[PDB]
Image (tube, rainbow, N blue to C red; front, side, top):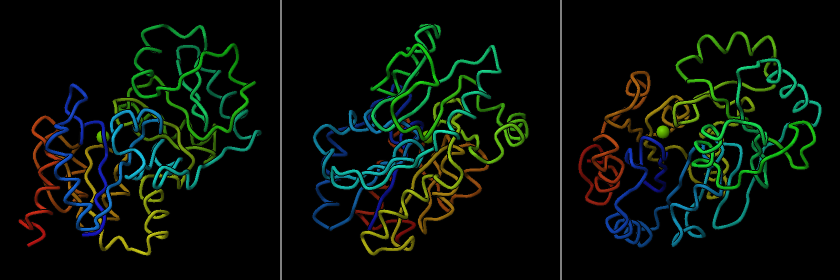
Length: 268
Ligand SMILES: [Mg+2]
């Protein structure tokens, strides 16, 4: 094991969105001593992710925005981008749905209509700490690489086909990690983001430990040699992952880290 990657909502975080900082801090210092890298891979905004690791932000790596933004040692390594024409097309399509509330995710900040219901904005603010109200989605001065819709992820199945023909591969729907639908650039998933870090570190999936719970973790868990599904993980995720651990309210992710440190099952 040379890399441990975890994803946040429903994994590293309990339902109250907190984690055991003292225990994790002690574990991290040991991982550092052993030269093992730590990576946070989540659909959440980069700026929201670092709020969870104030003391370690420049030491650990991040695969944010479900894979569209990657940071290593406090420095941006890569970011995806929709062409201006692509973003116009996607936004135009979303605007055709009158009951939809959504957020446009960019490099410098995320954006939401100044007229979107407060309840929706309040929920999104929990995942995008840099969230700016705009008067129009089409005049945004930023590079956009993701969208977050107020549609339940349970509806993905009814949504892929509609989106496939309306957007045609410009973007694909996947779970946001917190119950709703993210529209991402095809190929810019967590595994792809993790590969950029591995390539830079000259390591392989062979040395990777990944922990997840939902659909946006599929390629990450399929890629890692030591794949773990949280006890609360969705069925298809428990099927994809080779190993299991306790649920997110019982420090399931920290227990995987402990298994690495003490070399217990599955590490031998
Ligand atoms: Mg999750």
